[PDB]
Amino acid sequence: QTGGSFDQQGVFVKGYAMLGVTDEGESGFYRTTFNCNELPTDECLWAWQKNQDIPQLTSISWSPSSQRTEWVYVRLGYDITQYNFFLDQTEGMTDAETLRQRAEIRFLRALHYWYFLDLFGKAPFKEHFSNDLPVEKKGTELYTYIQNELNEIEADMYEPRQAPFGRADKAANWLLRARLYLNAGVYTGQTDYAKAEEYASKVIGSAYKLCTNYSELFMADNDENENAMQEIILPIRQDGVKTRNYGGSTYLVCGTRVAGMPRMGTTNGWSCIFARAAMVQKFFSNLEDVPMLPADVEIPTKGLDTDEQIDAFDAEHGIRTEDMIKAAGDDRALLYSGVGGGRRKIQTDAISGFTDGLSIVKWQNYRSDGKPVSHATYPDTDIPLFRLAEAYLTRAEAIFRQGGDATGDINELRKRANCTRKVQTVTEQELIDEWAREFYLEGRRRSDLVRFGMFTTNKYLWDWKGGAMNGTSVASYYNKYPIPVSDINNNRNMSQNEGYK
Ligand SMILES: OC[C@H]1O[C@@H]2O[C@H]3[C@H](O)[C@@H](O)[C@@H](O[C@H]4[C@H](O)[C@@H](O)[C@@H](O[C@H]5[C@H](O)[C@@H](O)[C@@H](O[C@H]6[C@H](O)[C@@H](O)[C@@H](O[C@H]7[C@H](O)[C@@H](O)[C@@H](O[C@H]8[C@H](O)[C@@H](O)[C@@H](O[C@H]1[C@H](O)[C@H]2O)O[C@@H]8CO)O[C@@H]7CO)O[C@@H]6CO)O[C@@H]5CO)O[C@@H]4CO)O[C@@H]3CO
Ligand SMILES: [Ca+2]
Ligand SMILES: [Ca+2]
Image (cartoon, rainbow, N blue to C red):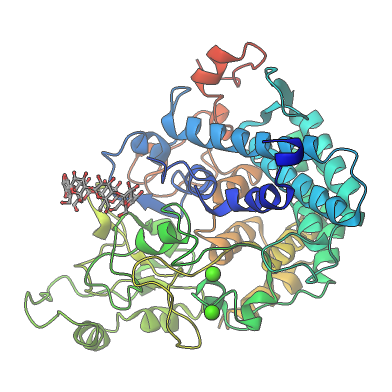
């Protein structure tokens, strides 16, 4: 529908909706990008390796026929066509409302192009909605286009924290540019840490502030709690009754839980996503310090049916998540090694099930204020896609790369997390580890690993990397996903990424 039937307001809203709503539950914007940036990393593992294309993503051994690569590629492209459609239909309109809408739609399109750039190093490009085949825009050109888009639309965007919650303001714009500049070395071959630092400072200097209780950023009321909202620069709205997405917060909550775990926050635990040993090591350098149930202690088959019973048993063996946090001396150590759901392992010699690694209870469907959530199954928890904390890590890394002292920005995050250990000296290792501690399971890991030259190389080997128990390297061409063979066959304008067949 166009012209008189074009529901501008409605299409505008749908533009944002594509971020959090949609099997069809496997192809959402969040799940596809999340998996491509998480499943192959040191942060987590998908427990059901029999699922199509899972071993590939898990071991960084996919090919151009990868179904999950096609899903994210096609999803990013579809979203952009919808944005191009909105921009074409509102082209020439000069009223203030439309100008703001167009600025935000261009922001969203820019965000999508970043994903193409970060994941594939290029993108099937189209500035408009039409039947013409997209043309290839790669590396530096794509990078330049995204930066220019963000630069041009800034003036029309909302002042920091003045936009209706869920919409992008100037800070979201600056944060994305800071992200682009930080990764400029990867996308253009020429770093630009000074600009990364500059834009990160603009975000830090805005009205946004850090949430004083880390866990609250990932709870059911993170859209009705100032403590959390003051830090969330761009949330993907999710609601238990109105906004459901099997690949949204439902995926982050249900997918990381299994029956028996205390405080599941949902009636359905999928037992899919769990932490790799390397993720746990981010909080415990010596994995021997990780609170664990002794191997010689049996788990009763009776008397462990309720949360209260499970907690008591975990308490006796010092394995409640609160005990995990205390031992780690870090509020972000939201892991679970308790008996709820069965005996957990930290590292496994074979990926056989959900209990082969500690559970990640970072995301929750419980309100910090204790009030009821809207649904017993689907979470109300919003996905804080953009958080002020990214500005601190981005500036810290940029400062470090430029030879400066980044202890301040790092300790700002460690202070917020009530860390017992403060950083005295910043190293590349501390930085990449802090990126994991702060943003694990938020869909960006791979990108940071590639930038640190640690995604495919021997520079950093984590458990099950490359398909080996103790980790092994893979070809460097794997730092970029391949263009789906389906698009290669349909669009002669697109060229396959180097290395792939
Ligand atoms: O550990 C569980 C499971 O986790 C993973 O799957 C999750 C998936 O990745 C998420 O996307 C989400 O899925 C939602 C889905 O997208 C929606 O479509 C909907 O699902 C509905 C189905 O479409 C609908 O058909 C029906 O499902 C019925 C099945 O069709 C039917 O076969 C039967 O299922 C039983 C299996 O036959 C049996 O083998 C056994 O399943 C085991 C699997 O073999 C094993 O691989 C693993 O499954 C993982 C999966 O691999 C991950 O990808 O554990 C299983 C043991 O529980 O038992 C099955 C149950 O009897 O019956 C079902 C139910 O009627 O119903 C659903 C609506 O519920 O909603 C999904 C969200 O619930 O979540 C899933 C986790 O469920
Ligand atoms: Ca409410
Ligand atoms: Ca919500």
